[PDB]
Length: 253
Length: 249
Ligand SMILES: [K+]
Image 1 (cartoon, rainbow over the protein chains, first blue to last red):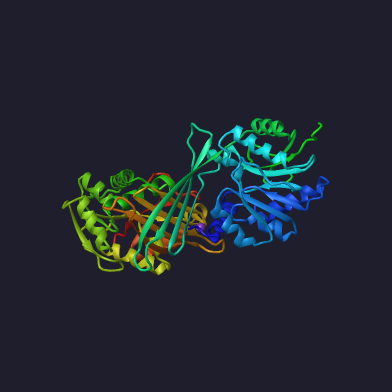
Image 2: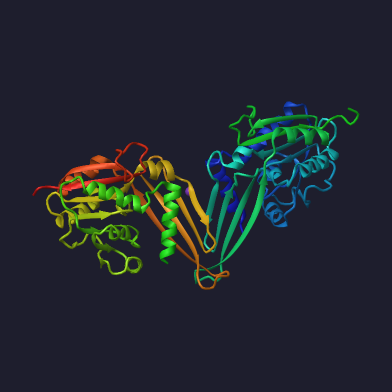
């Protein structure tokens, strides 16, 4: 199976070659966003924690983290990296979320897995249900220009000893989604170079600003600010990763 | 096996800008027709699986193909058949004489580190070339090794064939390293892949080095082109095509 070290080196490659934001900078921007808007944040809910790179940052910085993810195998890599300092649960969005969080975060472009705009709105509604008025929800999504391949084709691979992995991001010109073709080779026995191949395919969807703003406004986030990859500069046509900062409306409005 | 090597060449052509083999022979024929020396017998070094050998044979040349690997010669002798004389030679080593020209496409001169190693190969070719004959070969440039490849990864999963090109490059160097991994499936057709690996360092050579060794080897004239076209080589050239002309001595 793909260890946490291989996933980390995939993130390192996305930072160097694909313009992805390093995880310490994500947590820095997220902490600074909370303080700059007058938010006393102690408890944080993290949607789709993955292997726990963002979870590890939030725990080192002294937050009471609750991390959820649909994949049980990804949670095992997250509990090993962080430990018992964070609460881990298995939740596939959209689904009812736990209460008690001062802020909600969802990094690593996990929201691109939402199959449709309705599913995106249903997930945003589940977040607004557990957020008090004024609390923030910060997430990032890859843009259509990135998913279409305007900055080149994204592909990476790692040749470990008994394991080998290939991530091929393909984009058809007639669709608005990107298909991630994941290939895994596993050495049968220690000596012979015979391998077993396993292939999985996942789909990443794009959402324009009108859809994100309409679904967020319908879920109870009338205020939606979009930034360029965890910085203070605005989102432009050259933006590959958009950082959205939503603020929960007043329930009396 | 021959289909595996052909699909690897297809990837290099499509993804890295390598010249298709029919267009290589077009440039080679066009160059030969403008040097004032009748070319009929062609000594092809580094023939590999016979992709360039097939083009020279199809165009009516008497080809003598050689390669350092025996498994590569069997695939080349299977593709072309018997219309070429195949031999196993690993330069620097004595080469056969009697050819009107020498060609070596997709050359492995980037595996060589020192300029002396480049000079030994050029001297071996000049020994079996008469006055005025030409030596045509290609070389990968720093713009390809450092600029394009660099520290990027190229890989593909084509079902029965999967491969990985993992490049490593430092800014203070004139070379790059590549880690190659390959998985192939044959008669099983289900889930039985054979994995093989190889690692090579790829060196870059400046034009002054190539010409200095060429003049010392017996090639007074050394012309460089951009990837088997008549356009000259620039800073964006990824594959230089060199045309060396043997001295009158
Ligand atoms: K690399």
